[PDB]
Length: 168
Length: 174
RNA sequence: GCGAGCGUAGUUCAAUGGUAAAACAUCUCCUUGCCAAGGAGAAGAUACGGGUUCGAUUCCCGCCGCUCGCCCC
Image 1 (cartoon, chains in turn red, yellow, brown):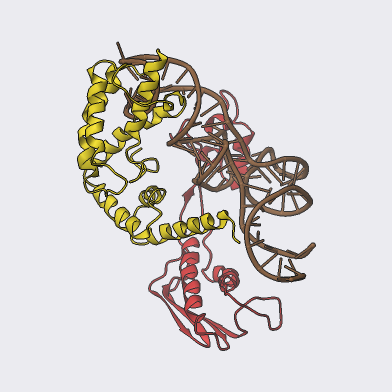
Image 2 (cartoon, rainbow over the protein chains, first blue to last red; image 1 turned 90 degrees about the horizontal axis):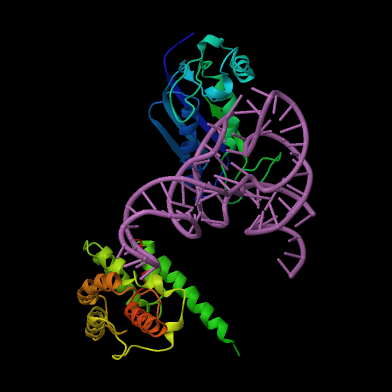
């Protein structure tokens, strides 16, 4: 069910970090995070990051509970290739239809380039704006890099051991 | 004992660092890249020449001089038979080439390797006008060996004036 | 040996599961003849091999060579 945009807090509580790594990490995190939600068509507000020798917090305000369910026009094969002079459309048209699960009548012609185009309208599969973060955060956290690193109980590279994660 | 290659290597390294320093205050890369291939000996001279030539390049007349000075340069490459001799006043053709040679002799007095660029274009502007008439009315095509050699030598010595001030190859206008 | 990054006209570079784009250099030509200056065209390419799909410069794997750490020093 749809609600209202509420705050989003991410904290990675580690042990003591060098004075010349908090500055780098608090930027590498926020700059790369204000991009993923744009990739996943999320709507945020004022994003700000904070650093401390024991935590690297990022606060994003007014994050919606849903994605923007909108239709997008794809770009299929050239019209000449997919449609013959006479008869039924060639194998490319049916392959496109069965790939995107759309009726044949939905195809329309728009003029661009030498061969004009073949175009179709498809949905975007709006999720619940929480599974996306669940599946994406393990990459945004692990995308940080440092000049020096170590391991404590696994094969994960980080500047200092991580002791807790507070993602709300 | 150190061979003579190490000193050249060090000079090249210092020149490459000087270029990096000079491109740090907003100087165009193609300008310093052209100045430093000829003024790399004294760093202060290079720094005071490349900081001023860029400022002069906005006089709206800079492309005119760039086009004219080295329009002759692109024919030099190829045949080198004309480098054997120099100019003379015996086999000279109609008064167009004589006027161009006189203008060249007049302008060569103010151009020496110890000059700066302040009066460079102001003295080179007078040479441009006879150049068009020359290239349009002499037919520098090599039909006679003597006249071809003489014309090639005259053209090379005309185009060799900036040898000592700056080069016009890495020039953007080209 | 052990990791990463790579590979597109001669050089520099565009894009994404689908008829390969642009500058520059070369060439063919139209201006009065040779360079400059205006125009038109031509040719020019995905390092290599395989797999799947109707179809990959794009996804997976093998190899070639380059660049950087580590190994050695």
